[PDB]
Image (cartoon, one colour):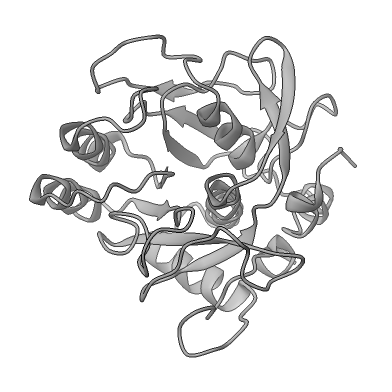
Length: 269
């Protein structure tokens, strides 16, 4: 129906938009630093905690990409994410600089503890651990907030932080179909993966742009889950992990892959 790159073509996201599902009624946070003001992204919520206040809308570029990767509106113009509308929020938790303080990632994982809706993505990973961050995830599970942190981009035999832990799932990138990408990171705690070697999406200034990375493919799984919760607005982040677990493809292996490809066709059907 819409025009999407091989990235969304393998996430069975169209077949879902054709079945009748719209993920409408769900809520997902986007911990980034700018979702770019665009007619394809409907800002339903947003809060900037980290210092350096550029603008609740736009300030870098990646953030906006993750936005359409979670629910780029389906108006036919521009790309098409997995979700059409849904409540796409904007939790500027990081600064356009490159990585807010732990007081930012913590205040962002705690502000979602209350208004963190049912889902929340974290396309970040600092090598600096902190119990302040654990106190934030503590506020996230205390209320039940499904988090799907990304992987990284090649760095030691481990994944992002928290990603690895914090009750946050960690996503990874893939190659041609499912093989391990070339710059995707790995570790003993990978949750899922997807195609992250080229992904055209929206951009500020009324323009679109293509980029490659596991950060873009991370919110692709975050959106798929959104559609699930939609079909079941009474379920919880737990019951959801079930459907998404047995629905998401399952390469196999002992832990490297173990569920790595996603498809809303088996999650909606």
